Length: 332
Ligand SMILES: CC(C)(C)c1cc(C(=O)N2CCS(=O)(=O)CC2)c(NC(=O)Nc2ccc3ccccc3c2)s1
Ligand SMILES: CCCCCCCCO[C@@H]1O[C@H](CO)[C@@H](O)[C@H](O)[C@H]1O
Image (spheres, rainbow, N blue to C red):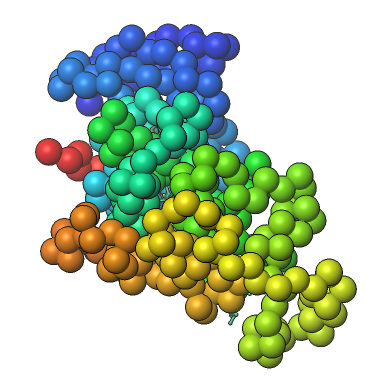
């Protein structure tokens, strides 16, 4: 190809097809609202910051682009376009990603509306539906939180990742277990759910040690079956040096809530990750009877992440990223 145009926005320089107009900053690496003229819809444009500065940077640009190109589901961000001003590989230095503009995050909705039980079902249902799709590609989100969830005026929701976070984090990620099953995202969904029922942060941790403290008051210190699975002797004693706590009865904590929502929370917010309900299982739970449709909860196409285990040169990553730009076929 098209013809590009240059525009300086808050000291940053944006070169984009003319297709997109009325570029407006949305804060922070830098995203702009824009008007797409080919369709007359509002978009969000992201300029990748310092994309190829290190090997690790370069691999991450490639990672994000491969990921976004693969995600094709109603409850997950999808790529509308990706472009570079560069006419060639030599010239390649910037990447821009295009997605549908949603002008509210779940945070902002929870500020000034107390959601009805029925809202909580539809919202959480959409998180699990997107999550079933992401998990079926063998991807873990790892940083699920209201500010990564986009919501429109029909309260339709999509999952994304802009790139305290700590409030929705699985206890295992914060003790650096390094394994991590997919249910770390289920833990996060539990924290989101409670805050939608309640209006308040389930675990408003002051810091990393305060975070863990609050989690254990609710869920309890590890029971005997859990300790049996803990391989490291230091970790075992570290767990034995924390004030020991009984599991609370959730019925007693979430006082006036749908008893089916309570029973769901009990299935998500379990210390032992092997015992958390999965996304697929939770879609089928009685709380979502009004929304559940087993024929409309699709899974992902095989996702090849063999790249995650390669150590390559900046310009290799760079060139792989370039192939991916060129081969983009936009959605209908
Ligand atoms: C798990 C899942 C939800 C599917 C995502 C992973 C990543 C990701 O790239 N990774 C790899 C990089 S990182 O390691 O920093 C995090 C995980 C997303 N990336 C993403 O959501 N990117 C965005 C965000 C806002 C946009 C605004 C306008 C236009 C374009 C936009 C694209 S979404
Ligand atoms: C005191 C707080 C400690 C947190 C207990 C974390 C238990 C999480 O669960 C553990 O997850 C691992 C994968 O991450 C699995 O290999 C283990 O089998 C599983 O029990």
